[PDB]
Image 1: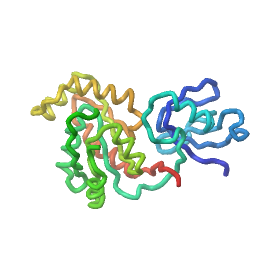
Image 2: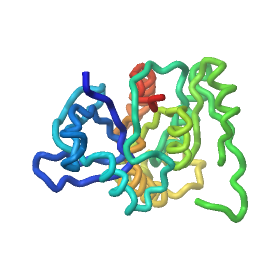
Image 3: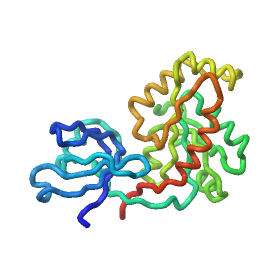
Image 4: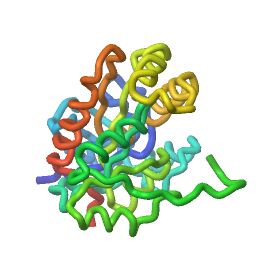
Length: 248
């Protein structure tokens, strides 16, 4: 009927009780432009995980959206509202893992299921640059071999991969505590020189500023290695979901 779907690329807080707040990356079915946006608002429905219709309310219209997005430095080449469409994944999506044991995760998957997973090589970081590592061709080589490319990349790389329509599966491994991290590292990678504190602080930063890129989250129990079996199921489950893709 009337409706179309959008993806937000700005954070917004409702100033009306009939409104809906949103984070970046949230999808909405715009159900009614409410007199062509002339009241400043649209009627939208929030789409939940497994694409179910969760909450209904008013959001800003396109003009006010574009205007609200001007003020936060959110470094994004995306429109404030992106026109968006559901599609079955037409290839094996690259997999990005974040959190205090993502390196162990990557290594274990590539070692134990070499037929399903392969670590994509990354470019050396250049001395005297920012906080372009994996080239697109490298990922294509792995995709064409019927495998998931494991990517050791930056949140900004993920954003960029989203923009180029490569839509990685992004898993966050959530730590219980700093101590938890230390304990898991002793058991899983005692040779590692990386700092448990640094990795824990980096995850807190990741969760707080960047949660909107996560496709899915697994909570770590530092007592046991159950996170691994759950990692393998989560990626398969994610690969089997329809994807929100840019329209046009």
